[PDB]
Amino acid sequence: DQICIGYHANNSTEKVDTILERNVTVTHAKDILEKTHNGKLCRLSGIPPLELGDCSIAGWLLGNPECDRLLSVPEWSYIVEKENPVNGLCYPGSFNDYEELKHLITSVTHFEKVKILPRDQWTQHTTTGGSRACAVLDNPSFFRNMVWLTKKGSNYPIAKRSYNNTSGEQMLIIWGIHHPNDDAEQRTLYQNVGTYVSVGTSTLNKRSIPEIATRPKVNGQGGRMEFSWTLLETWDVINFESTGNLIAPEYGFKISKRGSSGIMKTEKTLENCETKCQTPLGAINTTLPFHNIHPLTIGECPKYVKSDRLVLATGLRNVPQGLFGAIAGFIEGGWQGMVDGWYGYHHSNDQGSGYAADKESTQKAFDGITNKVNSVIEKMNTQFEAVGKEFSNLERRLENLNKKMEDGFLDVWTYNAELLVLMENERTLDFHDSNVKNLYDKVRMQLRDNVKELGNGCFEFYHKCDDECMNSVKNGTYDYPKYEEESKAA
Amino acid sequence: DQICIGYHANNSTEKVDTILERNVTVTHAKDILEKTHNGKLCRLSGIPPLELGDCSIAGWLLGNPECDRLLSVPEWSYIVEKENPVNGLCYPGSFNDYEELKHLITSVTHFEKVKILPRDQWTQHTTTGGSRACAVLDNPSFFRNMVWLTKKGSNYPIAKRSYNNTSGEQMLIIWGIHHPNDDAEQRTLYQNVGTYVSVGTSTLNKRSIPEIATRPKVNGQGGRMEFSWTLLETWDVINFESTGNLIAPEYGFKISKRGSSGIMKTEKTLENCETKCQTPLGAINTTLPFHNIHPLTIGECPKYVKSDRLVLATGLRNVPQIGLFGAIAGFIEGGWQGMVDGWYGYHHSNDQGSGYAADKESTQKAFDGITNKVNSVIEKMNTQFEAVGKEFSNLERRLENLNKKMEDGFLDVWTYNAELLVLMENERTLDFHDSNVKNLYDKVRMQLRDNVKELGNGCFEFYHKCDDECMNSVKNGTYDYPKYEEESKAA
Amino acid sequence: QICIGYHANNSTEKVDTILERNVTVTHAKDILEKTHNGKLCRLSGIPPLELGDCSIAGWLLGNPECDRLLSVPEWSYIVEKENPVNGLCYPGSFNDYEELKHLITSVTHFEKVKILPRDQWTQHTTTGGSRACAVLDNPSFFRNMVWLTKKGSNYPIAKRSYNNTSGEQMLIIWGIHHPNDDAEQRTLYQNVGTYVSVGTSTLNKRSIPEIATRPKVNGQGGRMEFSWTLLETWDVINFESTGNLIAPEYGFKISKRGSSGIMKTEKTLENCETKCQTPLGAINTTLPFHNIHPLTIGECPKYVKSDRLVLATGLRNVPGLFGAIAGFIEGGWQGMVDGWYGYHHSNDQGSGYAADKESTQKAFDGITNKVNSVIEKMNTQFEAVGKEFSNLERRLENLNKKMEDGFLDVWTYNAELLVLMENERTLDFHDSNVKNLYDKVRMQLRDNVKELGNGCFEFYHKCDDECMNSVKNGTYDYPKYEEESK
């Protein structure tokens, strides 16, 4: 007649690491590192991104002919370009504060193209000018949203037009100045040398002057076009005033913003799809606190880490057949044959044997570990972020500062997440150990001298312990006085 | 005759969370999150802030008439402004590298006004030019620290004046150029069309041409004034020259810096108050490592976190009566209301009485231990002076965003780590108490050996008479086993 | 009889734990690196560029004072004196200077070339110089640059170009001269309303000279404004000017792996090797933290605001959660040298100490994993902490400071607390190891022995060396000696 304290073992091969040990096999585990995505570009919190594919934001906004037909949703949650768009400034040049502009339209309400300065109303200038650099099929053309003002006959009178933003929303307006190859070209196109482009609003005062230099051809053009932009407040007016070289907008873009986002550089396309965390490889749908998919995410995302593996122990050390000496200790092996709990008893008497899980201690352990896992996951704070940024090539220092920052956080999170898992895994194994030792002690303190401590977690009865008796032990209501007399001999 | 091991219980309903459990009731606890402030704007380490009220820094430095009766201390540790200052560039315009200027004077020594270019000495120019965009009461007026040079009679001769910085300190100097709305304006003000403004020091070299162009009226003006600034070094000279459109300074500002600070946007005004950590809602007075009061602080501050609650268990699990080591709420089913003199102790019964006594040794151990734990979590926090809030122009959104992403970054790190630290430390504090009771019980057991019987929940029944002196020797670990058998009673 | 016990020694090593301060332990491991070699070293095989008291502009422009500089063709970082003495001897400025410096902190390789031989400026005077760049002490000039001035009394259009056929991107610098007055303009350039224009396939620029009275610097009221571009392979740069152009005669072939930084120090290269350099000396450590100096370059440990980070490895030195060590087993044993935990026995045959190498070995393996967990998990990517910002970039500089201070705070705190937490666990781990040992014997002997309460067991039967051995290894035969008669 004997009763034994034991613990669960199974066919698990799942390993974890702890602070003190490596590759420990445990009965149950849970990975808290998200490693999978759906390989798709999705809508973010219900809003699609703006898809530019081959074109750059400049090529699109200016209306580079290979871009001016782009579809264009009225509202988007982020922007998807390719790494290096083929179609941008068809006519070569530069764009002032181009990155700031990109950052501005990265997420919008609301965005709508509007005709603000009908091109036919430049009655004193020629308006049909174009370039072979922007040729189609294959006549010379030009940015579709813009107007190249040149002299009419031999005259370029001052060009003065204004527009009042009665639209109802702030309006993005873009304009440019042309820098010819030489003075002769300057005289041919604008008749006068020594000209200026002047743009003014309530908040903006900008003047550019043509800068003529000898340049290698780009897209077959030695000339350059330099563009600028502003936000025109509602009910405000913008005044264009130029004696030559102005590249005027014919259109403006109504814009409302909801906050900011980012550009995501990928070769993928939108699908009928919903996510809260987008990566260039696909979308993440996860509750886990960490992922290792891609650094450049957009949305409310888990923390990116370097690790390939973050597995928490939930079950106990799997010993098919610690701090507290019981598990894989004086109770040297686990019972492959206890399926109904983590800890329990095996009993032998005239009636049989023997496996019975302790429901309470098991229930307490499940609660405990459930809280552990939930602690590590739920306490992670998450807010919307767009990780990737645009910097120009005279902003390497700024780019580098942003890189050091993202690297510093990567280091902090990777280090802490690894050690957290190592520490908690250690303590989890010991938690189970403790639970078993306490179960073993409940039985001991009940039996005392009415049984012998057989070692290996077994108790040898000095009396006849029937099934009902065994149950009284298993439920902590064993009747010691009843089995005095019939004890050893006494 | 018996002696029982036990542990403190009390009235507390104070709750903590651990890694394994939520809302555990403990006898004592300490909040390590600072949640309160004094609702005052205060001096920062002895030094007051500069108060600007409704004026922006530009308005104040240029001397917008609405700002020209303003305090201005000899020295400040930060700048207080209202969220959107009413008074700035009264005549419409702009200010080059304005954010840098603002950052520069965020905290000064020492800040002294000097009349470097007395206006009355522009003898070949009209100097009393004013505008309705700066109307005083309610006559035309102008920035009181600046001089609008305009034609005298029908003439605007070349204007050349210079100044040597013999102030013995770096000097902040501001100047402007006027961009008229039209040629008639250029002509009225400066006679000549085709003018220039030129400014030169040892390190600064700048020449600008006025931009005449039609613009929407702001404060009734199509024109704009564009201001720039430089620091004139000790003993260096600044040369002004203009055939028109120069907005000259009459004053410069001797400036000495002892580090940088920031600007705090609030409606509060300075009070006779001292703090090391200021927020827009009021000052924080604390040694605690974390706070949740406001993100935009100035001073030496606790780490800001996104939690409502960070409570460390100090006492033990409160189990008043009518764990890893299995004693507390375990084989010793409950605690003792009646033991006030310690955390763990004994109850003894014998012929002479009974019998609560705190075990002094293990109680002291526990007090020292928990005291060190709390002190570890609090003292190890490195805290240096910072001004969270920053100024970025409307064309520095990427930069502003970089700043936001950084603060959010440390916010997430500190919040996650603080929440987890507490959960983990509370877990171990409960187990420490549990262990302490378990060890105390074992201490008695190992002394008594078979001179006593283990009775259940923490109690020993002696097989021999144990009077108060015997109890004492047990309580202080000098029990005398060989003396007490009489363990013929054991059989 | 037989007693369980643990190692003690003559250590005075002190560690702190979350619960306790100044605990003496048998052994401990410092994880904070505090020493450097006091030398300036090569970085993974490659030396720094050493500029003495010449600034980078002074060097690239060819300030006469910088002639005996002698560069290298490849370098891993740049060493500059805290405050260079030789920069723009002719007063002026340098557009996007800091971006230039950042671009050349680390190259492979670098080579000056004569892209625009000055002999070929046949329609201009090229001998112009200034007492501001005086050599010995006659007027001189930046040696890589060419001050063009009127020839006789004519300054024909200056028109030259260059095609980068050198096979490498080429750094090219030019300047414009802003004279002090009109007399100076005419003396130098004849013409008055002149320009300098520069063009490549990406660069477009036309500058007008600013003539204005300024304070004398190095005796000059005039100023030279320099700008730079990176010319692509097979691209062309075109200079055109009617005056005021300060032209390059040379360009610099440049290839970059990645970026580094500039170290300010007085020290000079000393023929050592390192993978982590501070301005005080190089660091050679496997440890995860260091407190030598903030501004490092290379693959460095995390820098922290800490004087001491000592990890306990051994046990409390006694010449805990489990109550064994410094508990019911009052003291350690000097005499037990082979292990952390063990036995002492008293016999008819003798005594005494025997290390239990199983539990010791399991412990050594455990602590070793802990230590190397703390160390190896640390990331160490190459980096250059120090950064250059101009005097109108204070906000950006302060933003960078805020970031460094941020990580420092995080790392200092986590490192301090990590050490305190792990140390309390280490001590309790040893305590538990002793307790389980004592219980291993107790649960074996059972009825056949007396538990004294000081770690000792007193046999109710004779226990010879062999019996003792079965106890010391968990094969003790309880039935064999069961003859009670206690």
Image: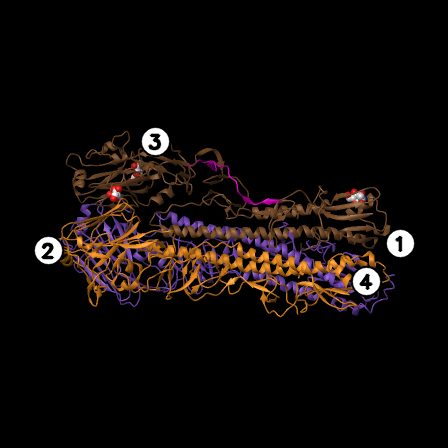
Chain colours: A brown, B purple, C orange
Q: In which chain is the residue bearing label 3?
A: A
Disc 4 packing (10 Å; few <14; some 14–19; many ≥20) = some
The chain that hosts pointer 4 is B
For label 1, the crowd category at 10 Å Cα-Cα, with few meaning under 14, some 14 to 19 and many 20 or more, is: few
Q: Residue C479 at x, y = what percent?
A: 82, 56
Question: In the image shown, does A310 or B347 lie closer to the viewer?
Answer: A310
Which chain is mark 2 on? C
Amino acid type indicated by mark 3 = Arg
Q: Which residue is most to the left?
A: C153
Q: Is mark 2 on a helix, strand or loop?
A: loop
Helix or strand or loop: what does disc 1 sit on? loop
Against C85, residue A341 (above or below) is above
- Which residue type carries mark 4? Asp
Q: How far apart are marks 4 and 2 (CA)?
A: 122 Å
Residue A47 position within the rendered picture, expressed as x and y whole percent measured from the top left: 45, 36
Q: Answer whether residue B214 is visible to the viewer in this image.
A: no
Q: Mark 2 points at which residue?
A: C153
C361 and B144: which is toward the camera: C361
Residue C222 in the figure: left or right of residue A65: left
Quarter where residue B340 is shown: bottom right
**Residue segment shown in magenta:** A29-49
Residue A489 circle label: 1
- The answer to whether residue C179 is left or right of residue B7 is left
Q: Which residue is drawn at 37% across and 47% down?
A: A391
Estimate the x, y position of residue A288 in percent, counting from the top left. 55, 44
Disc nearest the viewer among 2 and 3: 2
Identify the disc placed on residue A69.
3
Q: Let me know if residue A390 appears in the view.
A: yes
Question: What chain does badge 1 belong to?
Answer: A
